[PDB]
Image (cartoon, rainbow over all chains, first blue to last red):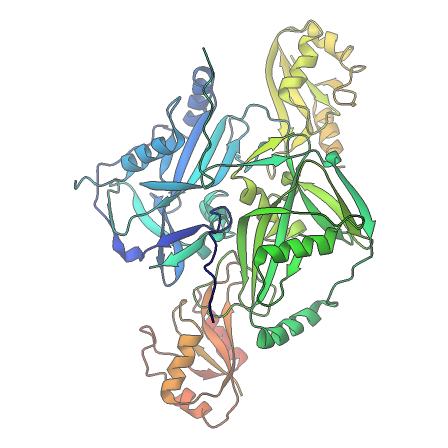
Length: 203
Length: 207
Length: 93
Length: 92
């Protein structure tokens, strides 16, 4: 018999994201990027200083997903064999979240041989000038020192990247991250869950 | 000199969500509802059984959020001293996920008095798959799996300003703040304990 | 030169904790360190409080209790490992 | 009857395993549980497979450890506590 034409599903209920073979993606070595902070305690010395004139820090990171063997992989950058960060960084005072993100993406990676960001996946707040960050603002905290916002960066069908010589662009399959904070941290390692709502397409 | 109105953002980029004081919500009681199963192992038997007749199992669960002290609290159906669960459960073969969840909320927290009660369910917040006929559930389908045994999907359920609910006389209802649950797999389970994060993307207003 | 302030709710905020203080005549609030569970970042119920004026510390020791921050009576007590140990044990309720 | 097929990749699904024996033409497979990491659900790279025919069991034991599944030669053995250990030694 006749079937009825499905009705439009609100993006809030069903978000459909297109994934492509991780083999579509490659890197060309680029100029090595140091980190703006020098030792392990220079970053907070800098955080205090900035928070005073600038105010609360606004960090953003991009999550770029590829796929292999029918499983989502997240693009991490490692350096040593124990350090993994998502591409992103501090925003400029008064800078737009996404626009700024594109600027940082294109900055840390990006084609020198000649960014779709529509989804927010999380927020993390750092209450004090210390390590711990949480997915919420503890009730006793009124002014958190840092706000980290994470976005799903829809990757193009094919892409060339520029990995600063000192970094290694690896593709982490979900089960490597899940329940493995010791390996990747509380943010990164909480992505498998944070991604599960998406209806992924394996092209 | 005149303020510029902040235009709406895309639903996919910022979801502002309205939270209200637990006190705005009043909670009565109703007929004690025992589980459709019983005894640990027994259920898995049924699952093996149902998986044959109906196929993969389809569970839906709603996440109701209140705010107290400007800090979201997830309403949890406690049982005993250490068993919490989200309101929800199995759908009936060939059933809209959401109309089913609605049907499970009224079923599970229905205001006995006047049943003119609607739920605003418009956000899915996660999926969890059970690979084998065992406890393990992961927020994803492991590469070596074709036919999962059970699929669990969670939807943020928006409470209106005020509304009256009703608990099965055999259950207690608590409002777990986020930090109770964060990194607390032992106390609440892999799923429930990952809500703090799963909600961290919503822009919460505390009325 | 610094004290402990406890029997605070886990929602008493650095800011409002400051409101109480200023409103004694004490205007030299040197840092405002809350104690908290790393696991979940929840206020342990007591904050280490600093002050350059070693007089106002009495103006708190005596005056702060008998004020109520969210229906709880503050507990200003000089810094010490047996107060340290006093509050840490109290956060276990 | 039951065996231990292993030395296969962690993405070797169950169906595409069934399709390997359907090449030897058995079709007896009754059950197929895999061994995985509880922590993350990843495959340890070997499974206890339930079969219902004693005869075909020979075909498995004998033959498919010659087929190239995803590049691997299935390592078929009987179900023994001393066999299991060599397989979980492969996780490491």
